[PDB]
Amino acid sequence: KMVVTLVVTTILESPYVMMKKNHEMLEGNERY
């Protein structure tokens, strides 16, 4: 053939950053 020759950190506080329902099932970016 042709031969070419040339992040965001947070905390576990309840009102600020809480884990939503089904956190064990859906975990990651869309979890908190």
Image (tube, grey):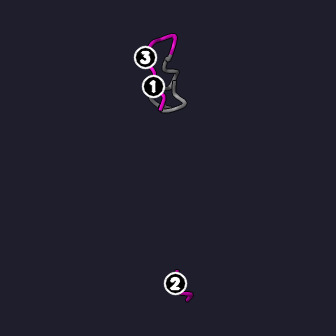
Q: Which mark, by number, is residue 9? A: 1
Residue 8 inside the magenta-drawn segment: yes
Residue 31 inside the magenta-drawn segment: no
**Main SS type for the magenta part?**
loop
Q: Is residue 19 above or below residue 24?
A: above
Question: Which tag is nearer the camera, tag 2 or tag 1?
Answer: 2
Q: Which mark, by number, is residue 12? A: 3
Relative depth, front residue between 21 and 5: 5
Residue at (54, 83) in percent of width and height: 4
Q: CA distance from mark 3 to mark 1?
A: 10 Å
Q: CA distance from mark 2 to mark 1?
A: 50 Å
Q: Amino acid at mark 3?
A: Leu
**Circle 2 residue:** 5
Classify 10 Å Cα crowding around label 2: few (below 14), some (14-19), many (20 and above).
Answer: few
Q: Is residue 6 above or below residue 20?
A: below
Classify 10 Å Cα crowding around label 3: few (below 14), some (14-19), many (20 and above).
Answer: few
Marks 3 & 2, CB-CB < 8 Å contact: no
Provide residue 2's location: percent of width, then percent of height: 56, 87
Question: Which tag is nearer the camera, tag 3 or tag 1?
Answer: 1
User: Does label 3 or label 2 sit earlier along the sequence?
Assistant: 2
Toward the bottom, the furthest residue is 1
Toward the front, the furthest residue is 6
Provide residue 6's location: percent of width, then percent of height: 52, 80
Toward the top, the furthest residue is 15
Give SS at disc 3. loop
Q: CA distance from mark 3 to mark 2?
A: 59 Å
Question: In the rendered structure, which segment of residues is drawn in magenta?
Answer: 1-16
Q: Amino acid at mark 1?
A: Thr
Marks 3 & 1, CB-CB < 8 Å contact: no
Relative depth, front residue between 1 and 25: 1
